[PDB]
Amino acid sequence: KMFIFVKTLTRKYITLEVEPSDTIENVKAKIQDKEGIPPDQQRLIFSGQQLEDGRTLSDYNIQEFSFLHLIS
Amino acid sequence: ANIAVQRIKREFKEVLKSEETSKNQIKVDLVDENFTELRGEIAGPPDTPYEGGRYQLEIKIPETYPFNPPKVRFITKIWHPNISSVTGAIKLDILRDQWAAAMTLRTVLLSLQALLAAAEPDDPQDAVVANQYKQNPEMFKQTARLWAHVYAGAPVSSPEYTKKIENLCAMGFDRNAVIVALSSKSWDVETATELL
Image (cartoon, rainbow over all chains, first blue to last red):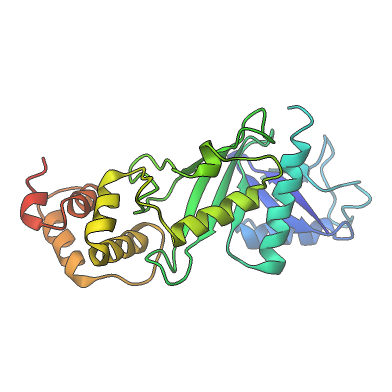
C-alpha cells in the first residue's frame, strides 16, 4: 500500500508500488519487470544492510517514500 | 529542505494514486532525492491534434513551493500557440500570474491537458504557431498532428507533409530543422529551403 524508490548506479530513481507484506524476491522481480535486470546479480541495500531473498519489507521496517540502492 | 516538502511528497503520492485507480493519463517520476526536479508525462487529450501522443515534462519545484508555482517545461516538442516550439516554455496563468496555495501537482498536469485541449492564441508564447492557428486552422491541425506523430509517439501521419520532409532531408539537412522550417514557412517547400 506504499511507494518506494530504488536508486540505480546511473542515479535514476525507479518508483515501485509495493505492500509491506511483499518479499524481497518479488520486489526484485518487479524491478526486473519494470527495467529488465534479472534477480540473478541483483542486491538491494537499504541502509548499510543488503536485503535477503527470504524476508519481507516489513521485517526490514521499509516504509513509504523509502530509498533503496541497487547494485550488480 | 524545509517542512513544506511534506506537501510535495503528499502531492507526489496523490498523483501516483490518482493515476492507477482513476485514469492512466498523467504520470510522475523522480529525478533527485530532495524532491526538487520531477519528470511528468501527460497523455494527449482526445479529439485534438495531440490525441494518441504522450508528452513529457520537466518540473522544478521552488524552495517556497506551496506558494510561487513550480517551473514546468516541455521536454518533448509540441506545436501549440501557448507552448514554445523550441524552448518548451509554458504560457499558463497558474504558472506565473494566478497560482494559489491548495494547488497540487496533479492539478497542474490536468490544467496542462486542458490547455492542450483548448488553446489561447491571444496570450501566446510562440507567435508563429499562434498566427497559423488564427489564419489557417486546418493547416495548424494537420501540422500539430504531424508534430505529435514525430515527437510524442502519435500513430498516424499526413503523407503530403511527409513527402516534403523526405525530399528536403534528401538534400542532407536535419530532420528536426527541416520540420521547424516547413512548419514555420506555411509548408512552402520552395521558401523553406530558402531559410538558411
